[PDB]
Image (cartoon, rainbow, N blue to C red; front, side, top):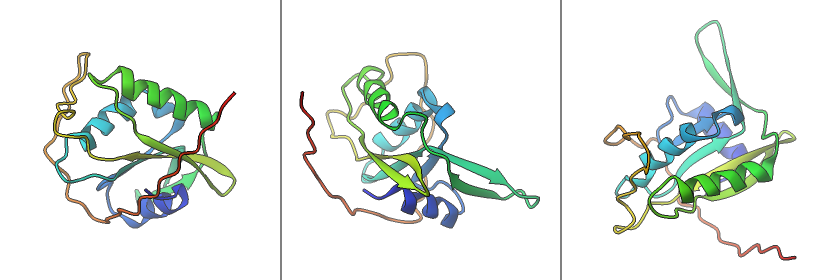
Length: 153
């Protein structure tokens, strides 16, 4: 895994979204979900990043500069996306999601590890065929930390 501040910098560093995608709060839904399937079906590409709460500005060159704007409700975006990834897919898939602040804006790091052999065949239970084979990896990351951060009431 990886911070949203470092992912935002990495989006600016890379020429194209190699294994790290950038997404706005309005992109929330199947537009996020088909991109998750595109990392889940990949053999040996464990550690694909989707960064939610990012905006981008186009220069006169036709250049894409990635800036922080954050989520309208940080927690609720992480709650809904867990529901999406459990209910839309044939099996309950957990994307490891963490809230990270960049310049006073709250963003969501969606860490997608590789699915197992059995779960894979991650097929959609609705009309929507996932297109692709593989995208060549530019920058690499495997800096994975765990924490059992449990809230109770």
